[PDB]
Length: 105
Image 1 (cartoon, one colour):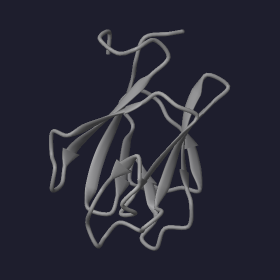
Image 2 (spheres, one colour):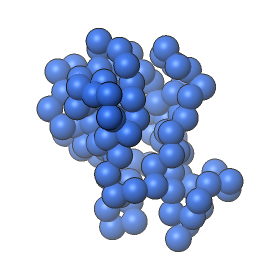
Image 3 (cartoon, one colour):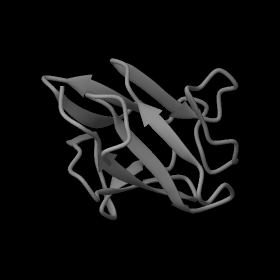
């Protein structure tokens, strides 16, 4: 995705309550959950208060499950963590997201 701040990435909701919504990943830790102060607020009972984190580490974005009830899935597989690649699908509750790489630093 050319039109993003250098070093950032984007998560797009492909399916779910807010299909079309998208969220910038441009910080060391981006929280995703039903907690009201989540950086990515996914307000559905299928989503844990603190469900996952998108972490920027060694110039790579990783998704980390932080003890969700239903799990965090990357390409349909539940993971404790995964280094994300362009086009990877991430499922958090009933939200189906795709991870898109942005421009380099």
